[PDB]
RNA sequence: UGUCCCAACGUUGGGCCCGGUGAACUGUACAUUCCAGUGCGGAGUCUGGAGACACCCAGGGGGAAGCGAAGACCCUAUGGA
RNA sequence: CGCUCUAAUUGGAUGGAAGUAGGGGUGAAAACUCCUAUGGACCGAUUAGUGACGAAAAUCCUGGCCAUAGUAGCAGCGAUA
RNA sequence: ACCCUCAGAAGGGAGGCGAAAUAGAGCAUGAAAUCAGUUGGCGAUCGAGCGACAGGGCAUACAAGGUCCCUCGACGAAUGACCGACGCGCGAGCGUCCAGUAAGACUCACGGGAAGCCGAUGUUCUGUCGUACGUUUUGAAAAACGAGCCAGGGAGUGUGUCU
């Protein structure tokens, strides 16, 4: 609820990792960022394998635990954490001043970062974060 | 004979104690033991002339 | 009604341009503490410097982060070695006769701690009249 | 033996002490910590309740194996050191006594400072299996109390 | 015939809470760890990740190659009996 | 570099020595030195000598002390008081 | 001594002696380990050889250290441009000139400023490096060996001969 994002990024039809990479780089420069339409972000690859990885991540674990998100919500955020030294003071700060949302709760339309967009016309081997989540068993709350 | 006036002996291994000669459970004779002999002491024999 | 130290407390020595620069160098550069390795891990191990002898010693092996090892290269500038931070060359003084031959411009005097208050007073007054500074002066209420 | 570790203005201060008391040095800590800042009069009431077992002494440092007590506040473990608490009534009885004999209102005096110190042990020996013997000592506690006008 | 199928309930003394008394083993240091990897090839401490708010009570003992004993086996000594 | 005692030369101390605590300055350093407090009688320097002369270690020796812990035991016995 | 307290020849308080009772009875001094109370720093969302060197927060009576901060300016090793002009390259971009110029560590001078202020000390945060020490070992952080901690003790000496 209410997040003064100096920058709002739209992930729709954007390569998750390429977005995450830049979103990290900015948050570490002190920028408050909000990622919008997570459920519509995409990651290239053969769907079947891609789901095997993510599914393997949900299954990993023991008493100590290995909490892995199922919602395209977390998925994106965990993807971004992996690009920040989240256990240092600086990093945790940069990670906390960032937020990912399902769809868009703002009025403004997010911008599209350069080099993160995927042309659906010249591309068929890719997957939607949402699609991934539905397989993992999440609750399509979007 | 200073420090050598006793039958102290070492129990050897077996009680988690260092191999030091003991008597009535008190270490003795050896140089590193309080009341022990003086390793290299002053000597009458030495020629100080 | 307030304390006032006796003698030329404010006196400064006159140094050639080279000495003064060399003095400033010593004051700027400084030097490592050179404390005995691991003196901070065990109370029975004091700070007094001892050459690490361990065949596997991490210091003796020069592993960055484990401390500097005493070397000649660490010496202070020939021209300023031993000088008080003021620029003066100290002279240990035990009585009034020790004040004889002392250049009040190049040297300052330090009264040994053993000397009593009676003898101190005499030393402190005649030193001043000789244009010499007393590094450890007596504070009298004036 | 100890000496007052704090400075006390004689015109507004009453002093007292216990010497070589063979009691729990660990309970003393607790009790002292607890009653500090209280009024000699509130203090006696408290300790008498502790002795009655209706009030418990927070055991914050020396608490291994100690059971929780619903009445402790902000903490969980606590007991009722009666022996140590009785020794503290004597101390207080003495300080309120010196307080009055000096013209102050004893009971109404704040407990400015109160500290226990372990001054030694009365050494004892306990025979054990296998023809061996071991320690079996008693701690000797000293305790300083400084009352002060409100 | 409760040795077993297959365990149940009960009795007494402990255990648990309170007052009093009051030890010992053990301790290089640090220490909330887990999964992998690496390393003198069997890591709470290295490396990558994961997890982890602090303190306390009871428990049964998985790990600390847990504690206890300078290995009795084996070989070596120009050792002993 | 530092320690003990000797000798020659030469200094300091009840107008407060040594030692100790905290603190300032020098030396690459062994170490030297000063300040404040405590202490209340001894203490140095230079040179030449002297030697039961420098410790973090030896399951080292002796003493003292903490965690363990307000923990185990103060129940178990055909005599349950 | 006396007085108050106390079951009390205990202890405590007040008081007396003495230069000193923090010289009060195992009583000169009174270290370290370590304990109580307390002050500074840190602190119940966060990672472990406990630090070295840098650089920040907070804290600090004097004394024994007195420096340090910002404008400008002087000097200025190695290194060394932007912009603009012209010419190349499919392109990223390069060449020539501007120019070995501007810049460039330290040091200094004028002016202004700081006294918790500079150093330094205590604690804490950040960066870099960092799995004790000694020993055994080809190889030790080692799941190889030693120590709970501290203090004091603890290991090339004498005679004879030779060189
Ligand atoms: Cl899990
Ligand atoms: Cl991290
Ligand atoms: Cl495609
Ligand atoms: Cl040299
Ligand atoms: Cl205790
Ligand atoms: Cl310079
Ligand atoms: Cl030798
Ligand atoms: Mg002897
Ligand atoms: Mg130390
Ligand atoms: Mg319990
Ligand atoms: Mg027997
Ligand atoms: Mg890790
Ligand atoms: Mg063996
Ligand atoms: Mg055999
Ligand atoms: Mg034989
Ligand atoms: Mg001479
Ligand atoms: Mg050694
Ligand atoms: Mg236990
Ligand atoms: Mg019966
Ligand atoms: Mg004494
Ligand atoms: Mg081997
Ligand atoms: Mg020694
Ligand atoms: Na991909
Ligand atoms: Na999982
Ligand atoms: Na004998
Ligand atoms: Na002789
Ligand atoms: Na505790
Ligand atoms: Na409560
Ligand atoms: Na409570
Ligand atoms: Na049965
Ligand atoms: Na276990
Ligand atoms: Na031992
Ligand atoms: Na600091
Ligand atoms: Na070894
Ligand atoms: Na080692
Ligand atoms: Na190993
Ligand atoms: Na022990
Ligand atoms: Na020796």
Image (cartoon, coloured by chain):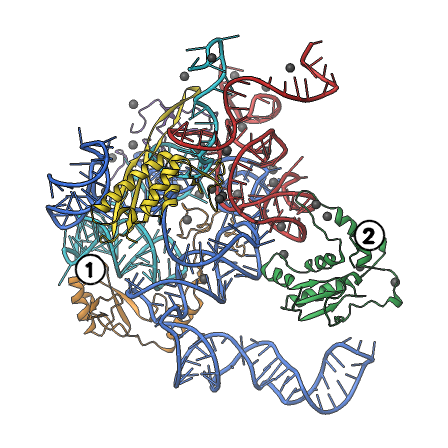
Chain colours: A green, B purple, C orange, D yellow, E red, F cyan, G blue
Quadrant in the picture for the N terminus of chain C: bottom left
Decide: few, some or many residues near mark 2? Use Cα within 10 Å; few <14, some 14-19, many ≥20: few
Query: Which one is nearer the viewer's eye here, A78 or C47?
Result: A78
Query: x, y percentage for residue A50?
Result: 81, 54
Query: Which one is nearer the viewer's eye here, E44 or C68?
Result: E44
Decide: few, some or many residues near mark 1? Use Cα within 10 Å; few <14, some 14-19, many ≥20: few
Q: Residue at x 22, y 52 (%)?
A: D10
Mark 2: secondary structure: helix
Which residue is label 1 attached to? C115
Quadrant in the picture for the C terminus of chain C: bottom left
Q: Is residue C23 left or right of residue E47?
A: left
Decide if ligand 24 comes within 8 Å of the CB at mark 2.
no
Q: Is residue B38 visible from the viewing direction of this image?
A: no
Query: x, y percentage for residue G22?
Result: 22, 47
Is residue D104 positioned above or below C113 on the image?
above
Mark 1: secondary structure: loop
Does the residue at mark 2 contact the one at mark 1 (Cβ under 8 Å)?
no
Q: Using the rendered view, name the quadrant where residue A33 is placed.
A: bottom right
Query: Which one is nearer the viewer's eye here, C33 or C75?
Result: C33
Give me the chain letter of mark 2.
Answer: A
Query: x, y percentage for residue F32?
Result: 30, 57
Q: Residue at x 35, y 41 (%)?
A: D45
Query: Which one is nearer the viewer's eye here, A1 or G50?
Result: A1
Q: Is residue D36 left or right of residue A83?
A: left
Which residue is label 2 attached to? A135
Query: x, y percentage for residue D2?
Result: 28, 43
Q: Residue at x 43, y 52 (%)?
A: C36
Q: CA distance from mark 2 to mark 1?
A: 91 Å
């Amino acid at each position: 609820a209410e997040f003064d994002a100096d920058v709002i990024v739209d992930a729709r039809d954007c390569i998750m990792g390429r977005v995450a990479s830049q979103v990290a780089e900015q948050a570490l420069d002190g920028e408050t960022v909000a990622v919008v339409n997570a459920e519509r972000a995409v990651i290239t690859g053969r769907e079947e394998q891609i789901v095997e990885k993510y599914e393997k991540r949900v299954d990993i674990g023991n008493d100590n635990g290995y909490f892995y998100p199922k919602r395209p919500d977390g998925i994106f955020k965990r993807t971004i954490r992996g690009m920040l030294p989240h256990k240092k003071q600086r990093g945790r700060e940069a990670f906390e001043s960032v937020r990912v949302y399902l769809g868009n709760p703002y009025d403004e339309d997010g911008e599209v970062l350069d080099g993160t967009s995927l042309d659906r016309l010249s591309n068929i081997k890719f997957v939607t974060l949402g699609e991934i989540s539905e397989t993992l068993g999440a609750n399509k709350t979007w | 004979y200073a420090g050598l006036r006793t039958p102290a002996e070492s129990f050897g291994s077996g009680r988690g104690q260092a191999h030091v000669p003991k008597l009535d459970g008190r270490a003795r004779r050896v140089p590193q033991a309080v009341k022990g002999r003086s390793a290299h002491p002053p000597k009458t024999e030495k020629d100080r002339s | 009604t307030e304390l006032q130290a006796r003698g030329l407390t404010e006196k400064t020595p006159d140094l050639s341009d080279e000495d003064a620069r060399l003095l400033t160098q010593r004051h700027r550069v400084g030097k490592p503490q050179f404390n005995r390795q691991d003196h901070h891990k065990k109370k029975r191990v004091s700070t007094s410097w001892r050459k690490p002898r361990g065949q596997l010693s991490k210091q003796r092996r020069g592993i960055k982060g484990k401390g500097d090892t005493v070397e000649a290269g660490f010496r202070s500038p020939t021209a300023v070695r031993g000088k008080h931070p003021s620029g003066f060359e100290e002279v240990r003084v035990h009585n009034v006769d020790d004040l004889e031959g002392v250049d009040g411009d190049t040297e300052a005097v330090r009264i040994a701690s053993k000397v009593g208050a009676r003898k101190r007073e005499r030393i402190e007054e005649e030193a001043e009249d000789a244009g010499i500074r007393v590094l450890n002066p007596t504070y009298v209420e004036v | 033996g100890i000496s007052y570790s704090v400075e006390a203005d004689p015109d507004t201060t009453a002093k007292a002490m216990l010497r070589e008391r063979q009691m729990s040095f660990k309970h003393s800590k607790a009790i002292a910590r607890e009653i500090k800042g209280k009024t000699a009069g509130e203090a006696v009431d408290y300790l008498e309740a502790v002795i009655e077992g209706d009030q418990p002494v927070p055991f914050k440092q020396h608490n291994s194996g100690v059971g929780h007590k619903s009445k402790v506040d902000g903490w969980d473990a606590g007991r009722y050191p009666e022996k140590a608490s009785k020794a503290f009534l004597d101390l207080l009885e003495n300080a309120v006594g010196n307080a009055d004999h000096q013209g102050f209102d004893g009971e109404a005096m704040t407990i400015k400072h109160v500290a226990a110190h372990k001054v030694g042990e009365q050494q004892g020996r306990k025979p054990r299996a296998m023809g061996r013997a071991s320690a079996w000592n008693s701690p000797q506690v000293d305790v300083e109390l400084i009352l002060e006008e409100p």
